[PDB]
Length: 192
Length: 205
Ligand SMILES: Cc1cc2nc3c(=O)[nH]c(=O)nc-3n(C[C@H](O)[C@H](O)[C@H](O)COP(=O)(O)O)c2cc1C
Ligand SMILES: Cc1cc2nc3c(=O)[nH]c(=O)nc-3n(C[C@H](O)[C@H](O)[C@H](O)COP(=O)(O)O)c2cc1C
Ligand SMILES: COC1=C(OC)C(=O)C(CC=C(C)C)=C(C)C1=O
Image 1: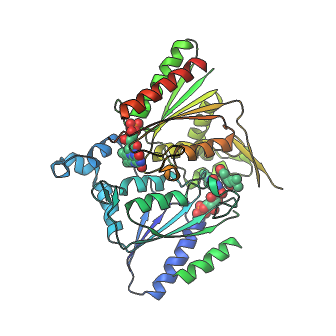
Image 2: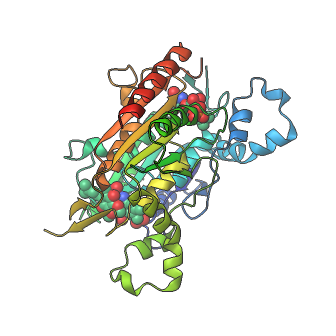
Image 3: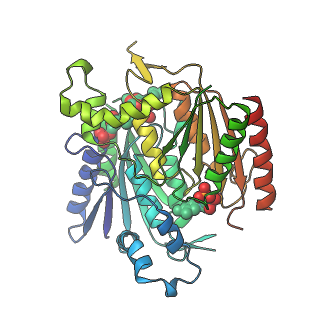
């Protein structure tokens, strides 16, 4: 199983979402020694936002006739999509930032949801892929049945976006109160 | 009554959310010649993302003791927050990108939600908003249909509903949403309706 790990926290050593994700990846590597891991940093690296140029090229009515300039505008997107195609398991580590994800992760999603590549018209085009979302939160009760579940626009939105392109087998492991981390940690070891 | 307009679409003349928002601002201008209008571009301008240095600065236990480097890391945030404090009405124009907002608008939000400035907390964490007496108008454009209340795809909409939650957290709980749908394809009717709604809001604000 080939893995694509997308880290969304701008923090490095201090990132809990990053740490917990690495705990899973390490535990998984031991259980599957032949596994490959590709890491795509979107937290500590400023992934470019969608531009009007991107929109013109991505939604170009006839893709084959794109100019070299248009292809250049889509070069990063193609690289990012390719990493996704080449993977079997998608691991996303992300904090909750203002009831959603950090802007860098939104930028990544906006690059890999591509007409005619990951979706068409609406139907998904990705198949046989699973996702694991490892998230960290300062507050409490954003999970299923929580007092503040309706305010959660982070992982539940990722489900929607990922589901739209065909990734419908998604698991979310969440730590709150920043004991919950230990539960998350142990949970992740079992999954690996 | 002072207005802050935040445009989130990367498109210019062809941005429908920008166009509709400008219809409101112009109509408002006609009814209030003395009113001040400030524009903050987050769509055609790449707003910096929250970094680790920003987190270290914004959550510093003794904010008075921040080094000049730390203050530099917060200089943009301080400017963005200030524009908001100076405003009575906030106008956000935004597309729906992949069931949420463009990353640039998310970045703007992440800059203006600030500990001890736009929100605070005490330990008993019990959060408190610090903005008062302000209102917001969200003008949005969508390619598909049914993302509004009662719509078939309502549960998929993580854009304007999410903006409501984030804005409410810092104290802006009076929020109006004007949406146009079917841009991908009727749309002329949706736009005309949104226009009439905005012209009415402008005349009465
Ligand atoms: C800019 C910013 C926004 C945040 N917004 C929320 C939030 O909306 N809800 C919440 O529960 N925690 C919020 N937090 C707290 C973080 O989610 C929490 O500290 C988390 O552990 C960070 O994960 P990390 O260690 O991987 O960086 C926020 C933190 C920052 C820096
Ligand atoms: C990257 C991208 C993602 C989009 N995602 C959605 C979507 O999830 N749902 C939808 O109804 N329309 C979606 N659209 C269509 C836009 O919402 C629509 O074209 C809108 O009018 C753009 O706003 P603007 O005219 O202000 O630029 C998307 C468009 C782009 C370019
Ligand atoms: C920095 O910004 C924010 C936090 O920082 C720690 C939070 O914990 C939270 C969590 C709030 C709840 C209701 C527990 C929010 C919402 C937030 O915006």
